[PDB]
Image: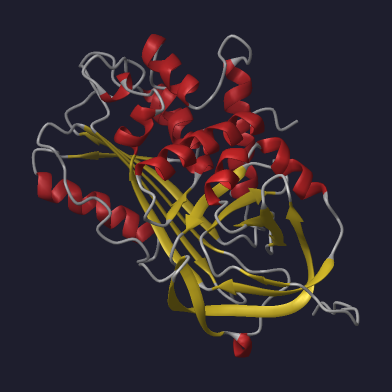
């Protein structure tokens, strides 16, 4: 091992804190892993400063970690996420759309399909409306209709577009009962509430109040190789929570094997996040691959090339089952832990400890 996990975690937090500062009003949900994998794969077609800018933007110190170890970590991670036995029910995809007039390098197309198990297509960008249709049809087919009309605009000068999508519908190892789901208040702020569907269950949870984070920290395992970590900040401590989050704090939580009783209230969630990666990753220092000076000679040898379009959409559903453990609950008052106010969450792949998803819910029904 998990050599690149600390870098992915730092990239995840840099990405989250930028999105959180740009809008303090919207639900956030994105996949650090899928974004970093897409651009680690893209770097194979870049050289020199364009290449170095991408790997540094993904929080890799190129003077300390060899590039071979970087790609080994991503391919090893893509391995655990894409195996036929996975109960994770995780559908991710990366589509590369290149102008049909370009002479493509076979090494790049081979590395993209073989090493990173991604898809590359040629498209007539002279027909902008038909190019957008083929791109959106690919994403809609890849998500069985979950993501429709991903791309809304394409510039006329587009010759290279990247789409990265990921859809997650997890199944809890210890599920909620549908009969127990009821409408409850969600405190969008200290004086305002909205009604949301709220799951609840009495059980033995990996849960604790953390004075360091001023938050309740709930960990719940999915069927498969992933764990959801929910952070419920104390009154007025949301910003304090986001500032303190580090990878080492996450690791300590994952190692805890203690369970305690609690009456958990957790909202049903169906949230999405759509991000312009050119704008977003440009704030993280990745700019040259999107500019006219881009060194994409690994993709096409003769003609100039730049990445004109890059979009990420992540979709999350949280419900009671997602599709027979008996827990012993003591005769004692369990704390009432209600996720009925803005909270942060992370999904962690258990093998690599990599951050599959990161997000914040400010309002479950603001769809």
In the visual, does 219 lie left or right of 109?
right
Residue 69, percent across and down?
63, 21
Residue appearing at x 31%, y 19% in the figure:
288
- Looking at the image, residue 133 lies above or below residue 37: below
Residue appearing at x 31%, y 14% in the figure:
295
Quadrant (top left/top right/bottom left/bottom right) for the C terminus:
bottom left
Residue 292, percent across and down?
21, 18
- Looking at the image, residue 326 lies above or below residue 113: below
Q: Nearer the viewer, residue 271 or 300?
A: 271
Residue 115, percent across and down?
53, 33
- Looking at the image, residue 224 lies above or below residue 35: below
Image quadrant assignment for residue 52: top left
Q: Is residue 282 visible?
A: yes
| Residue sticking out furthest to the bottom | 179
Q: Nearer the viewer, residue 187 or 7?
A: 187
In the visual, does 304 lie left or right of 280?
left
In the visual, does 106 lie left or right of 256?
left
Residue appearing at x 82%, y 77% in the figure:
325
Question: In the rendered view, how is the structure colored?
Answer: secondary structure
């Amino acid at each position: 091992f998990n050599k690149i996990t600390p870098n992915l975690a730092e990239f995840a937090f840099r990405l989250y804190r930028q999105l959180a500062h740009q809008s303090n009003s919207t639900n956030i949900f994105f996949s650090p892993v899928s974004i970093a994998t897409a651009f680690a794969m893209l770097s194979l077609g870049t050289k020199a400063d364009t290449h170095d800018e991408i790997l540094r933007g993904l929080n890799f110190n190129l003077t300390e970690i060899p590039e071979a170890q970087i790609h080994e970590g991503f391919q090893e991670l893509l391995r655990t996420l894409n195996q036929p036995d996975s109960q994770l029910q995780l559908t991710t995809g990366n589509g590369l759309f290149l102008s049909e007039g370009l002479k493509l390098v076979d090494k790049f197309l081979e590395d993209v399909k073989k090493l990173y198990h991604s898809e590359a297509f040629t498209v007539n960008f002279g027909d902008t409306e038909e190019a957008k249709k083929q791109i959106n049809d690919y994403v809609e087919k890849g998500t069985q209709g979950k993501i429709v009309d991903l791309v809304k605009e394409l510039d006329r000068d587009t010759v290279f577009a990247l789409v990265n999508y990921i859809f997650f519908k997890g199944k809890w190892e210890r599920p909620f009962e549908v009969k127990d789901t009821e409408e409850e208040d969600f405190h969008v702020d200290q004086v305002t509430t909205v009604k949301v569907p709220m799951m609840k269950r009495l059980g033995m949870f990996n849960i604790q109040h953390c004075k360091k984070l001023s938050s309740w920290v709930l960990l719940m395992k999915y069927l498969g190789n992933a764990t959801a970590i929910f952070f419920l900040p104390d009154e007025g401590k949301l910003q304090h929570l986001e500032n303190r989050l580090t990878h080492d704090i996450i690791t300590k939580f994952l190692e805890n094997e203690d369970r305690r009783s609690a009456s958990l209230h957790l909202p049903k969630l169906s949230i999405t996040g759509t991000y312009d990666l050119k704008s977003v990753l440009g704030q993280l220092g990745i700019t040259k691959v999107f500019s006219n000076g881009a060194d994409l000679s690994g993709v096409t040898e003769e003609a100039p090339l730049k990445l004109s379009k890059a979009v990420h959409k992540a979709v999350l559903t949280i419900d009671e089952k997602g599709t027979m453990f008996l827990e012993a609950i003591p005769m004692s008052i369990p704390p009432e832990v209600k996720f009925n106010k803005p909270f942060v969450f992370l999904m962690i792949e258990q093998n690599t400890k990599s951050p599959l998803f990161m997000g914040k819910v400010v309002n479950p029904t603001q769809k």
